[PDB]
Structures are given as C-alpha cells and as structure tokens.
Length: 157
Length: 157
Ligand SMILES: [Hg+2]
Ligand SMILES: [Hg+2]
Image (cartoon, rainbow over the protein chains, first blue to last red):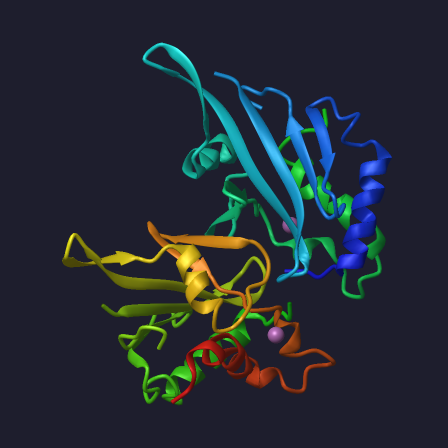
C-alpha cells in the first residue's frame, strides 16, 4: 500500500478535473465530479476490443486505507436469442477482457456496493510503486496514479 | 491505515495462535491456521446478539494494502413455513446486528469472494490508531488490532 492524506487527494482531484485531461481524452465520453468533489466518474466511449461495450470508472478515496480506490464496471451488449440486450459485465469476464494485456489482478476479489450498484475494485498493482522513500513527489501522486491505474490498460492514444 | 509488512504479520499471527488467546476464548468453537500460516479462521459459539447464529471470522493479510483484513460471515437459522433452516446472512442484517452494538463501519460496503464463498470485509475504523512514530510498538501490532477489530464487538471472556 501507500498513503496519501485526504486533503491532498481532494485538492489533486479537483486540479485534475480542472486540467481538462479527461475532457480532452478522446476515449472518454463524459466526466463527472461528485458533490463533495471527492470522486470522479469517467464514462468511456464504446469500445469493442478496447457487441460493443461501455466502461465506467469511479475514482474514489478509501478512507480506511488512505489510498485512491478505482471502481470499475462495464456494460456489455449481448445478443440474446438474436436480440441485442445490455447487461452489467460479470467480474470473471472483466478479468478476461483485460488480462489479454496486464494479466495480473492483485489480491482478493472485491466487489464494492454503492447504493445498490455493483463495482469492481481495480488493483493491477501495489500503489506503493508511486511513492519514494521520503514522499518527495507527493504533489503529483494522483496524476501518476492515473497513468498507472488507467492509462496503462486504456491507452491515451 | 497503518501498514505492517507481511513478514511481521506472519510472525505475529503464528505467535498469536500460539498464545492460545483464541483457544481459551469462551466464544470460540474452533481455530484453524491456513496451510501457509497466512490466515486464521475463527468459528464462534452459537449466539444471538451474543434459532441461533454462527459467526465466522477469517483473519487475513491484504498484500494490496499491507494491512490485515477481517473477513466476516454469519450463519443464521430462520424459520421458514415453520421449518428451521440455515442461510448465510445478508450484509444489511450483518450491519443491523453489529451496527446496533455498536455503532459504526467505515468506507464503502465491501464484499470479498473466496473461492466462491462470500465475505463481508469488516472495518470498524482506520488502522492508523494502531501505530506510527518510528513504531516502537510494532511488534504488538497484531495484538492491538485484535483488540480493536475483534474483541471490541465480541467481548473477551
Ligand atoms: Hg504499481
Ligand atoms: Hg482505530
């Protein structure tokens, strides 16, 4: 693990949102900042290999672990009896959709339930990669975290 | 959170098991150390508020967060059409059982899937109360954690 304090997360999250980085990301359909500005929902544009899908990322702060928490869910279209239908993708399939690159998902399967909605805790790696010995680089934590936890499996380009 | 490295967790867990603190605990039906001595299963004696329940606690280590995880599930006997039957308890009720006495859970509702079994990750609070400050008390740390995460809502006896 790592630690970034909440005040630092809050600030960097607003700064990131303001930067327009997600707004000008061509992948990204729309961006939303929660009321507390604690959290950010990204909706990716329709993707087939990355029968179309729609990917949702909820960027949040875990107050228990003091680290960002990336919540994942995916809408899949599926032909049922010849009829196109939409369902929420099941985790084991999310595990296939992805590893095809980044074959490793860390730790234990973890479903986060948000007011009735089911999300996947996304953990390709240990967030401790992001910090150095002395925490010198704290100011860019979130930005670099984005590169590792998001851009790495969904290319900016 | 307050991180503890796997080496120290592993030692203290095996050490905790040795003290027989769980074996002589009145509430405890049985204690099992997983094959790797990584994790510890506690089955508790039949209770209702402390047709009866059966509570299971799995003490494990998160490599993602470098913190212990208390995994929790509960067998409740319900009377269905007049016939006693058992079921795994729903999280809302696990809350309304624990949450009433009392009284808290931090963060989002987290479900953990172990080889198909469903566990509710139990966080009465952040672990940042357990250590810090050059950590002269690190060695205890699992013992403090047990006091805060387990004995607080169960009661040592
Ligand atoms: Hg990493
Ligand atoms: Hg605490």
